[PDB]
Image (cartoon, coloured by chain):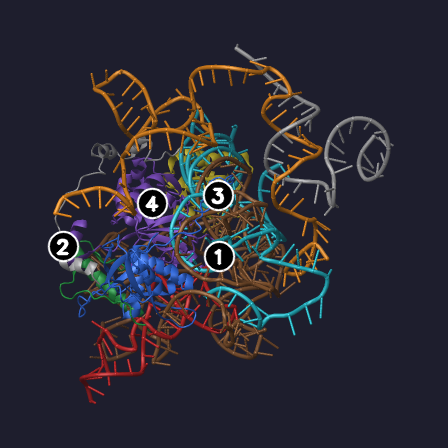
Chain colours: A yellow, B blue, C green, E purple, F red, G cyan, H brown, I orange
Amino acid sequence: DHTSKQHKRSGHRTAPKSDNVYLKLLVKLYTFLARRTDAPFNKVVLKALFLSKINRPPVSVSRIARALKQEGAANKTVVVVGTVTDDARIFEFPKTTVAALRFTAGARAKIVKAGGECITLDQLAVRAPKGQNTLILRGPRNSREA
Amino acid sequence: AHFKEYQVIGRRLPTESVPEPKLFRMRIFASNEVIAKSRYWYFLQKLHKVKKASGEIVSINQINEAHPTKVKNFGVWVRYDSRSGTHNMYKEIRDVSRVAAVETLYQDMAARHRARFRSIHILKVAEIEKTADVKRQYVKQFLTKDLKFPLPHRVQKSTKTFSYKRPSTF
Amino acid sequence: IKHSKCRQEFLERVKANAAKRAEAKAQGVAVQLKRQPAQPRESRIVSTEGNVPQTLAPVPY
Amino acid sequence: VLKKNPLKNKQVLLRLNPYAKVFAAEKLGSKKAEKTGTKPAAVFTETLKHD
Amino acid sequence: IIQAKRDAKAAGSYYVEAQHKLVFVVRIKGINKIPPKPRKVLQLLRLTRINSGTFVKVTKATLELLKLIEPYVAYGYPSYSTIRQLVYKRGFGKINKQRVPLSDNAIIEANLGKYGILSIDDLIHEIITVGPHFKQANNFLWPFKLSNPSGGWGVPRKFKHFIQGGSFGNREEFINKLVKSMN
RNA sequence: CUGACCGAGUAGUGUAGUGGGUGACCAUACGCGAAACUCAGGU
RNA sequence: GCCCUGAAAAUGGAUGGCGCUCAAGCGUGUUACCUAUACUCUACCGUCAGGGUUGGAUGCCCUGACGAGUAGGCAGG
RNA sequence: AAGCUCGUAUCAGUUUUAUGAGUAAAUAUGUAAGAAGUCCUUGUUUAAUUGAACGUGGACAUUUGAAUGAAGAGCUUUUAGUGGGCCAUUUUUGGUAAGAACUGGCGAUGCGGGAUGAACCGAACGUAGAGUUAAGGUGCCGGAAUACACGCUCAUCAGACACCACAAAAGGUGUUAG
RNA sequence: GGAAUACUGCCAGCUGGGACUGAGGACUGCGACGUAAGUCAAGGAUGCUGGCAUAAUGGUUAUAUGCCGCCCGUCUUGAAA
RNA sequence: GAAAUUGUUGAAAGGGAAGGGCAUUUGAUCAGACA
């Protein structure tokens, strides 16, 4: 006899659809970190890495400034799983460290000019294995036409 | 296997303004305690306003035969529900105990009247100590003094499937 | 259209449970405000000293 | 790897319950009772045999 | 209990045992052609498959549920020996999401010591002697997978009430005999 | 206009049988379960 | 309670046949016997789920449940 | 099918507690069993911040408001087939001998039994080894007792196991018991 | 008045015979017997022996027999028709 | 130098069908390894 479905698959992804070699290395590293650290930051980053391109909207550099203006967030490191796109609407960018998979040329130039330092996810994990002093920003999802 | 006799007493669980009812009792014939209690409840529900939910069995005890080894002429009064309307029936069974008499009565009712257990009601069973009051001939004939009869046409049983002697009877 | 005592008794029982919780907090004891279904009756002694148990003898026929 | 069954292979039974060893000493199943002369009451006996 | 019974008998009284607070229910019918109401009732009792049973607390709520599934299950009052044999032979304790046998007291302690139960004997005591944590112990125990009764069910037709010579219904004291054969 | 072991555990009804009966219908076991009605009181 | 009539057609016919009468027929009671792909114990393939693994990683090990199927969907070959 | 956000999760083809709905049951049908709740105090239409309303201070964290069970709950995109089905059960209607409302099956279903069967009784299916059963049977075909025990049958078309393809009243100086 | 037996249930009482399975693969853990050394029926078979070393076991197939099995596709609520 | 179809030689079966499935006997045939 049965009450639920005969066989039910897990409601979560296991590996990204993309075949990028570098992305899979980051996935492996973050899986290891989450399994051997149980840090919620590592689990969240691992889950975000499996999101599709549509489910990973870019985060404007102005949106990074938005979070940095929060009380006590001026020194917090900002981590964006998606891509950091430039934004000319902001004329001054606070000096901060930004970690993301990809940085646009304009955004990277603006960050360098503002005294910041673009960093990859692996380097961020090396600096913050447990995700201490880290801020996660997710780009708007309703913005994409749907 | 054989039928058992149990004395079943119901309490009709008391409540304020209704304390300690009269503790009605009955004599029930059944193979086990559960069937005896079920039959007691069935009779009690029909006799007066009582129910299993609003009642309990005070105590059940098996009524062992006082003299298990003694031939008795048991008088039987039974109400059996046929396909048509039910009617009274009086029978006499020469048996050794009440349990055996009731067991034989059940088979007799099932055979001679097709009356199943569900349709058989045991009104009363009483041992008949007297002899002149016996009314059924088939039991009366056995009361003759120095009664002796043969067993003509005795048939034996053979273990092997083949016999060479061509056996006979007696 | 429907407005009956169904909910009113619920609020009354809520108030009673709150009072019982206050009592059990003031005095150390199990709160015991959780309703329990009817439980089987416990054992007791029954005596026939008052009335002899009559036999019914289902005669009615 | 394999589930062993208590009530036999007494090693497993002793492993699950050390009291089993004490159980065997007196055997805890054939303890002698104490006889009493609590004769049944007259009313009960009369109601049992009689109707 | 027996001493009280003897005292009542010797003093013109009839002692009555307290209504049993624990019953054992075993599924008797298959899955096909089960009306939705009894099917759901059996599902709530974890009687997933035939020849399977679980311990049920005796309450007016559970009694009404048993009333509905009466034609499809056979139950009664188990004895201490039957409960002990069931726990020792078919004893499987529920862990996070898997059915793991209770092969050691450490396993029981690591998953039920929160309520003071740390050995198979303690679980048996809590089951037979219904305590405050009876529900926790009952849920922890996996439904028992019981074999068919060795020697047959003893009746020509199973699908009849025990009072009517069948298999289902109330077999309060005879449930132990059926369980022993099926265990 | 109220109480009742009062109608009555009656009518009626859910569940099960490879239960009976050609059919009409009926009985059993697990349950639920009334009203008119009856006595007294009320007005 | 059992039996006959009540229950009359057209090729020859079927409690299924053989066949049976203290039945191997009918009602009922008591026992042991045969088994389904059902149940209980175990071996293996696969699906699913929960854990372990930095010293072939989509990799390897442990545990638990399950395997019907037309139109049709997905996945792996 | 793809998944997304949360996660002990609120739930349940089920019961219990309370009561509407009914000369009037039973089965069902409706609402609740509270942390998103309760209480003391207090801020910003009535003669009066009197009160609604949303806030602050204070009192209770989980026997926290019944039982049982839960391979978690919600959410977004998109789409292959059907849109005429058949059988069976209950209620109602019609009726000398079918039309509406309910639930389970077949259709999509194997396996054992009814000598076979789509509507029946069991039971739902991975490949294997051992054992116990279900319905169905123990004279042979046919694996199992010409088993035990109590009563009935002489049938010149007896009888021989629900659905199965089915008759009674009545008559008999056949027979058994009341 | 003194006893057993019958029925029923328990025994973490003893024991004979028959059938299937030998799955895992250096230790790690839970237990028992022992003053100890150690042993054990304690998280899956070991010890000894005999025949053959080949068509002997075994696979394929021809055919002998126990039982079963209707003719494929489409359509039809339904076909072997 | 394929199948449908046909002849010669060797083997096997055949009482109003054949063909197929689980299971074994008989005939033929067949691979492998041995401090």
Label 2 belongs to which residue? E10
Please state which amino acid type lies under the numbered disc 4: Phe
Chain under label 4? E
Please state which amino acid type lies under the numbered disc 3: Pro
Label 1 belongs to which residue? E33
Q: Earlier in the sequence, mark 1 or mark 2?
A: 2
User: Of helix, strand and loop, which one carries label 1?
Assistant: loop
Q: Return the x and y of residue E130 as percentages of the image width and height.
A: 26, 49
Q: Return the x and y of residue B29 as percentages of the image width and height.
A: 30, 59
Residue at image location 44% in from the left, 36% down from the top: A31
Alpha carbon distance from label 2 to label 4: 45 Å
Query: In the image, is I60 to the left or to the right of E147?
Result: right
Residue E140: mark: 4
Camera-side residue of I81 and A118: I81
Please state which amino acid type lies under the numbered disc 1: Lys
Query: In the image, is E12 to the left or to the right of E176?
Result: left
User: Of helix, strand and loop, which one carries label 2?
Assistant: helix
Look at the numbered discs 2 and 4 and tell me whether their residues touch, using CB distance below 8 Å. Answer: no
Q: Could you classify mark 3 by the number of other residues whose Cα lies within 10 Å: few (under 14), some (14-19), or many (20 or more)?
A: few
Residue D22: mark: none
User: Of helix, strand and loop, which one carries label 3?
Assistant: loop
Residue B167: mark: 3
